[PDB]
Length: 207
Image (cartoon, rainbow, N blue to C red; front, side, top):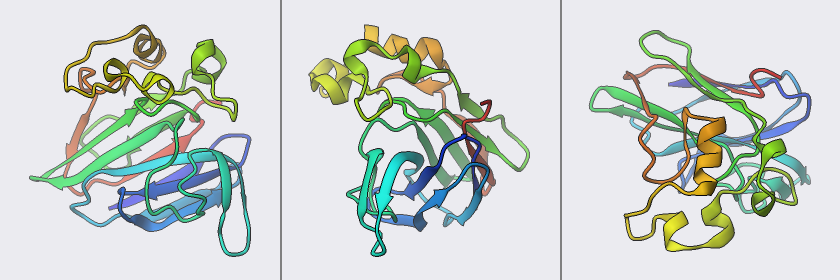
């Protein structure tokens, strides 16, 4: 499958794509405002994620740091990024279907549209100003809005026992972005697409 990753933000983003134990394609790249990066993801990929990182500095060897979404200080991510990270999530070619979603379970840093470029299913979007509205206790100093599990580390926020309910913090994410997961047992906002669809992730889709 092919994914076009488009930075519509007015600021530079460092895109990342990983399946947790390995990079997808090159795994990461600088995207200036307006730049597009097309990657090839292998059919049958399970648990892929795409996200944006902000305020990064890297050297020549590709080591450095980002203020949101850092993946162990590498430009080319091999594993997942440090919250807060708005997450595009996908599993491809699972019994003839593709499954996509946007997730706020690891917080929010950049607004995002996640849409197919082929036919047969709708896209999902989380483009509200979650950072600006972020509750005081969840604001990440580096920018972005942390999830309650990252901040407080309780069984309720992290759904550690497999049972947990909505919280005042999860309801904040859900009210601004109903189409994204707000906690682990949120009623699924997953979209079912035909197998081997193609996709576009757009950062800052409206502004």
